[PDB]
Amino acid sequence: SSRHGQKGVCSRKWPTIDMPFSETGIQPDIIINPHAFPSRMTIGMFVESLAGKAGALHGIAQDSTPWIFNEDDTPADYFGEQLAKAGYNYHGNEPMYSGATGEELRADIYVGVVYYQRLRHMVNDKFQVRSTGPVNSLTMQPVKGRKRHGGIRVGEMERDALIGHGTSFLLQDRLLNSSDYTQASVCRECGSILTTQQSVPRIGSISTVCCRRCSMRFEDSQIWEDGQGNKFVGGNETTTVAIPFVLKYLDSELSAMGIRLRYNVEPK
Amino acid sequence: KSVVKTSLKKNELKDGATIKEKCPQCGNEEMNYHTLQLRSADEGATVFYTCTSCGYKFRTNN
Amino acid sequence: IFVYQNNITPSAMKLVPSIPPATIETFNEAALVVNITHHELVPKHIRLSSDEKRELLKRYRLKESQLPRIQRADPVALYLGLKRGEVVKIIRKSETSGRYASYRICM
Amino acid sequence: TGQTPIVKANLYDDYGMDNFPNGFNAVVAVISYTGYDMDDAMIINKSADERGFGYGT
Amino acid sequence: MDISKPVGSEITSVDFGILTAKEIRNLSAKQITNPTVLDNLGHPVSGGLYDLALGAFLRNLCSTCGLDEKFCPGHQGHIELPVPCYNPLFFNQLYIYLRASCLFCHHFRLKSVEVHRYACKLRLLQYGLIDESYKLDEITLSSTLLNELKSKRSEYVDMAIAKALSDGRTTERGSFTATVNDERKKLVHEFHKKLLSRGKCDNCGMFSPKFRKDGFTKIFETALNEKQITNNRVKGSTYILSTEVKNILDTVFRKEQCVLQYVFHSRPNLSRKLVKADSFFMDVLVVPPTRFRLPSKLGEEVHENSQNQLLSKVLTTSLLIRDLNDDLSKLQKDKVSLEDRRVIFSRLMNAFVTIQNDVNAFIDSTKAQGVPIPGVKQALEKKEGLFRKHMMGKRVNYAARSVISPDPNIETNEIGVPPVFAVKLTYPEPVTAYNIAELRQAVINGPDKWPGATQIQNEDGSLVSLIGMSVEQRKALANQLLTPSSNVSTHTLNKKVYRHIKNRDVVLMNRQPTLHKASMMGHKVRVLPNEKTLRLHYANTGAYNADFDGDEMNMHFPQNENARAEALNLANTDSQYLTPTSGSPVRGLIQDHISAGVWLTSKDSFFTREQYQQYIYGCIRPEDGHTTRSKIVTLPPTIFKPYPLWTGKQIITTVLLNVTPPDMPGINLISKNKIKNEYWGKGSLENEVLFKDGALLCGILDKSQYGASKYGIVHSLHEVYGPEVAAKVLSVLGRLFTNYITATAFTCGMDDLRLTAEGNKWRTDILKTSVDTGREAAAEVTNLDKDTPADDPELLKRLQEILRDNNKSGILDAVTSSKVNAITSQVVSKCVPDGTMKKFPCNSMQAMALSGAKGSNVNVSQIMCLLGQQALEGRRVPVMVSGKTLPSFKPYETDAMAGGYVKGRFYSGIKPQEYYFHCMAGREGLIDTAVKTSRSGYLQRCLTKQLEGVHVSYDNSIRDADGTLVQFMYGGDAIDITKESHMTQFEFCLDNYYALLKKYNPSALIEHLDVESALKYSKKTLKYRKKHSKEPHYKQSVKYDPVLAKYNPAKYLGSVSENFQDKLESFLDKNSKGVNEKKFRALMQLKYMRSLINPGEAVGIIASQSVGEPSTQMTLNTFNVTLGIPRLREIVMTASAAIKTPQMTLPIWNDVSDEQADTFCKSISKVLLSEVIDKVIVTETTGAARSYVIHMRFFDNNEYSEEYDVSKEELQNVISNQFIHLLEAAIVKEIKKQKRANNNMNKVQRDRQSAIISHHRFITKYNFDDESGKWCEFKLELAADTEKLLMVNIVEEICRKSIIRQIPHIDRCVHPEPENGKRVLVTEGVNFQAMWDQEAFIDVDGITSNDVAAVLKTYGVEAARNTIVNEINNVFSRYAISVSFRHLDLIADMMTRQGTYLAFNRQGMETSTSSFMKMSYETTCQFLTKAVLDNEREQLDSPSARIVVGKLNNVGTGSFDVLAKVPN
DNA sequence: CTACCGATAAGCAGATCTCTCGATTGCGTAT
DNA sequence: ATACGCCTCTCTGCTTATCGGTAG
RNA sequence: AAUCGAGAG
Ligand SMILES: [Mg+2]
Ligand SMILES: [Zn+2]
Ligand SMILES: [Zn+2]
Ligand SMILES: [Zn+2]
Ligand SMILES: [Zn+2]
């Protein structure tokens, strides 16, 4: 930034030979677009560049306290007389040539020296990229934070904009297929998500997914055991759907409220 | 009851601020204006262009 | 149709649904000096017969209740004597498309 | 590497700001030449950058 | 998600129920007993909260399933509450039911036949039979009579339901729509209101004790009084235990199951199961698994989880009660019962209260009595909850964020991807025979060299990483990258390689706040070699609302072919050229390219052969595909001798000729541009753009041609050659204007900001006229003589009064501001552009202000001519209490500069005072933007929550997600706004006829259509409409309807709008111009058929965005009637009946004169008694009657009668009747609080005084100026008992209260100037039935009013919808923001879909089939209890429910399914 | 006459875009 | 030293008290 | 993990 609120990120580091060069052989170290001024209206930067060029020529310094110049003693006239008395142009313009082709530019370029400050918002503290990595505890979703290797949030407004496109596979890919896609097991009979469990496999027999709500106690080949060895028979009518893990966590939080959700499986 | 002027008529108020913008409706030279910075401390300005003949309104940033 | 001048007692309102299969409707002489259909904001309301109502429902594959609903007590249904279940035809003079027709149901 | 401003207020010296320079004097061209600086961006000479222009730790 | 792991089963729907304590223990894996989370040795105890039963904890196998921590799902557990507790969710309903039940007969305190009527009506409403529910009340004719009545009711219900099931109007599973739900909810609400309003039972007639409510967990009762006991006798406070109330409610429900099975259901109970009262009581508590209760391990800050803390608290109370009830057991045998058994009983009761409150705080932290630990409800309630933070939006994988930096060397559809992202982001690519050429090379390249691959997924799901491998290993792996499988289990799968993001991939950019769908587009990837910022083209700035001053944009990389094809075709940036908000274009070059274009396309631009060929090749580059001819083609030079000289318009022409495809003509455009003709010389025509067969012949290419301008060249190229060609045109024009701006650069400097000597002379001469504008404005505002000196004492006195009074200050600050702004405009017009020493096109400041590249004539005038008056809000700069605007200015300064008129300019700097005022203004601007950022939206969220399902169906009717219809036609014409721009542009269509014909191709679009019947019917309808339509809308008859009603416009050519056809006929009539009119009409009709909105278009989302996103551009509220976001809150978010500023629009008959209209205004407007009294003189005289003589002075009759149309007799009647009674009421209220000119009567006045004395409590004297009507005096005599009264403040308050005359709800009728030539009166209140009296003045046919509730009351639903649309359109018009009327129409139809004035809030969405949408919206608890009480099964139709379950949406590409065609 | 209602007046519950850093997180009794 | 027990400035609606109108 | 402060758009 300059001392006139003319901030702007460094876009590209232009090669010196590609930079425009003046008749005196100097190539500016800063290029500022002329379109920054008409709306911002920082004429102080213009008059400062004028005075800085004049001061760097004469080897002097010029005070720029406000209100020393008035409607008669115009700073443009003052520093322009100073610029002319060193051979340069009264308006601060310099014939410059294009360093890309070589020909002279159409008009005289406006050059000068202005005081430039380097702000502290460097770009090495801003970029972040994540493909896979650490995930949250109960939701199995990306963590927060640039420094912890976390994903970024697709929020409510992003979801609303992704629906409005009619982009539905895209919306599912962002919200589900790449956030907390889980292929859980459901009870095709009792219609509950997390009431089921893996049967503890036995020597010879193969493990299978079995229900714990549609299973009746063996004391009250369709049997299976637990880790505690308390075997019992139960319905093997259990399936595999694709759901978010946050659905399972919400179903737990709903069990904590005494509220059950019955998910109906389309093929029975 | 007072002695000062209290009431301002609609007719007697000439909002002023005349500029020579081109009217998108009719083409009358006069088209009043007002600028109100929006959406940031750095975003561009918008001007409430308003004709004086047909009453057309135009709030165009650029 | 019965019209009354100023007020209605509860002892009269208690007989409106008391006499089937007929119907009695009540209006106030006041707040009637102006027809609510002549106001330019109110579209032309045309009561629909059942014959075209079933046709509309089969054309759009609709139940009765999935239509936009018109209140049984709003002045248009009061004006038209519209009963429950019989849909109505509305000719909305749209600013963009000119004229088009939409169908509410009284329910 | 900081520098004192060529153009400065009188109070710059009174408050002894030269003990803590804030910016560098640079030759700035008000030119539409690049196409890579339109809204607010700006172009920095690559050679100046290789010569320590605006360097910090 | 892996696309090689198909899923068979789906969640087709879900239902809400109660988890009974029996099934919990049935489904439990272990009971929790002791609050021993972790003992010594740092391990969990057996049977504790962190048991090995509830999952695998740390390095311990789960004791239930025997798996590791990472593969144990987490089994459910429970604890046993020894005493049932009130569930803090069902407590409201349980208390309401309890408070209306009879303890003796175990039936309700309501009439049992009434209970049967409600049960029958609810059984009906469980199906789609809402009409018969109201026809049931028609069933009217003790035990035998009531049995006959109830049997008739039941049989009518059953026969009607059987008929409905038979004839298809319902089914076995019922019909639950929004109207059905509304009727059912209303019935049940009044049913509970009926049950509660009971004094005595009706089955046994025995009074039951009332109850008192103190909060939660606690219910008491009160004893019966004597009268209740006597009736209870002749029939033949206290704590109540939880088991006792459970028994009460069990008996009540056992005896009323018949009605309760319909009260607690909305669908036919196909399971027939009973309704058990143990639902409301938590006999057994369920603990979440250890997986969901794990503790945070922050270094050694391994703190207990909050859920385990609350559960252990409940467990401690449980163990306390368990150990206490053993002590009571032995103490009971000792039989104390008065000294120690009662002590233990008190302890047990307090412990029961404690454990119930512990469950209460575990479930809800809100109700905790005595920072707070969050509960389960607080885990779901608000934005920080679970819906709005982990289902409505989630952190995602394969994304990246970075700062954007500009790049004009990418192709406007691409994004410059830094190589640092290009090595991380990957895409799963299954190998094939067409892949092992380059996937093999990527695997050889490895994880670092780009393009390369990081991971390889094997056939059996093994995931192999390339990160650590060596080159030999990578070579061997890529050698085995496609090998036949000896394992036949996965003989249907191929290996997937996680290749790096190459150039053919597509990406999804995003910039928060994502306020519209265009702010999330799809970009192709161009992988750049150097930097670490994403590179963006300039055309993507009006869409993202983005600058390049540190903005950062999110980048999402889709991982499946379906999302790839979505972002390439549906969300891609080429399709987003026009915003759906109004159809105006949103892409274009911005500033540097605009000024470069103005320079290149001027008459002074000439280029040699080398310059011409270099420009053309540099911007075209046929190796990438910009050219459509495989070889660059040029034009002959404009000048042949002396040497060849192409021009700039030939550069434009050659570019167009190379991008525009062959086998098609060029654009014939006739437009304008911002730069006038007077700025180019004399006789110039450079303002008129002109194209002709693809060649620019006139005019400069401006912002009007590339940018945000309709009907410019890029817009027309879009309309004629599709969107991709306009994409290429913007890209190539960006390259051309870039390579040209390096050759001949553009600058700006101090010479551009100067004037001439005579220009400065003109400026100073005009500004020397501004030495007296302020003083004259003051001299006329103070109604003084002109030429009065600025130091006049009278002027200073009046100016001080103006300073004291805010309204007079506003008058002064308006008049003076007007005069000084006139002076400013004179200066600006005189000195620009005739004063600048450098002129356009040389003057770059003026050039970019004229071209619209950046800046405005206001800014140019500020830099070069004048800064002008600074206005803070609507007035000038603040004035201090001393009359000083600043220390520098003397008190009451009649100087323009003192009041803020800055005559300086930014070229020559401003004085210190003007600098201070300018700082005031700038600070005001920053404060306004602070307010806007603080209070910005939530209007869009409230709209989009309810409109997110509305979409266009294959029947072309727009309708909610469940199926309910909103509109039969999107806007009444079903045309798309992103395609509606040039439909009415008949001149453009005619001129480009041949190209448009080649793009529409009726040859391949005429076999599948019908092109006879629609045209025939349209002709008949137009003939009938021509015959009529001189008649009023209420008099016309629909013999013929609109054409769009009958024929599907996408299938029947000629079935078009009723206004489009009329306008096309008027065009073809008023200009005949060689292509026959028949072919042009056929082309226009095929264009209309192709301009139709696709089925599946999210009209609801689009309308919500179109009403919300433009509303951020109006939330600045500078300058009575509510405007902007407050008005939209009233209309859309509240639907308040009480509008803040109600108003009425009352048309006047064209014969009633303006003076008579003002007389009508005076006769209608309210006038209070205060507004006619000058002063009131109260003369107290305590010498024992405290007399209170009052002498109220009136304005002169000739004044107040002429000002208010009030007569002396009317005033006297008001005084004698209303005011004195009001006064004495106030006096007696004050006393009650306090105990803690001539009278030469004419005997008519004497009778009047006697009447007043008799009718009034204190009056003793009274006399009115009957002859002159100037005063009124009366003595209000009192007694010495009473202490002092003000008797002046009392009179002032009563005088303000009392009203002389008033139409109800009207306080004023003001006659404004006509708007659009129509005479209208506007009154400040809405009371329709009162203006109908004055037919002779007001056209009551045209009386429309601001309020929507009033209009809905007195004019019906459709008038309410029309006034809704007009109101929500009036807000945007006053901010000059265009919103397509289709959007507002859809909003209005959604709002009034129930026949009422709904709103977009939580109260406005009570009636809705899907409960997930409301639960995710807000008040999750209230919407979840309401859902589980009604057992409301939702079918997963709204988008939000789809997200929550995780199913593919319905809108857009979810509108249909895809089936294969296996040919064997 | 008598419930029976009811127009006030009064109490109560919920919202008010994304991102990056650092600093700090409590105290009285009794063996 | 160390383990038990604990603390002054918004704004929509929905829902209820309270001391009196209101048909039969 | 909550707050506090600082900032970026
Ligand atoms: Mg920015
Ligand atoms: Zn089961
Ligand atoms: Zn005009
Ligand atoms: Zn387990
Ligand atoms: Zn009873």
Image (cartoon, coloured by chain):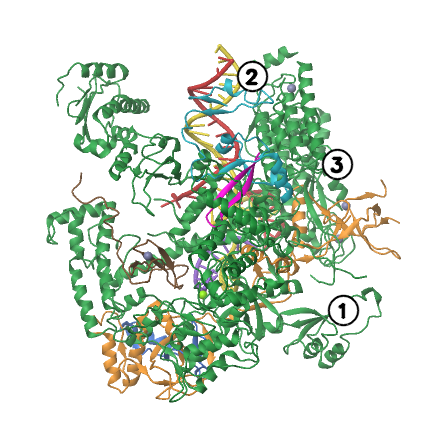
Chain colours: A orange, B brown, C cyan, D blue, E green, F yellow, G red, H purple
The reply to whether discs 1 and 2 touch (Cβ–Cβ < 8 Å) is no
What residue does disc 1 label?
E494
Crowding at mark 3 (Cα within 10 Å: few <14, some 14-19, many 20+): few
- Left or right of residue E888, residue A105 in this image: right
Q: Earlier in the sequence, mark 3 or mark 1?
A: 3
Mark 2 vs mark 3, CA separation in Å: 46 Å
Which chain letter matches label 2? E
- Left or right of residue E512, residue E490 in this image: right
G23 or D41, which lies in front? Answer: G23
Tell us which disc is closer to us: 1 or 2. Answer: 1
- Left or right of residue C48, residue B30 in this image: left
| Residue visible at 42% across and 46% down in the picture | E1127
Q: Quadrant of residue E685?
A: bottom left
* The residue stretch that appears in magenta: C87-107
Q: Amino acid at mark 3?
A: Ser
Q: Amino acid at mark 2?
A: Asn
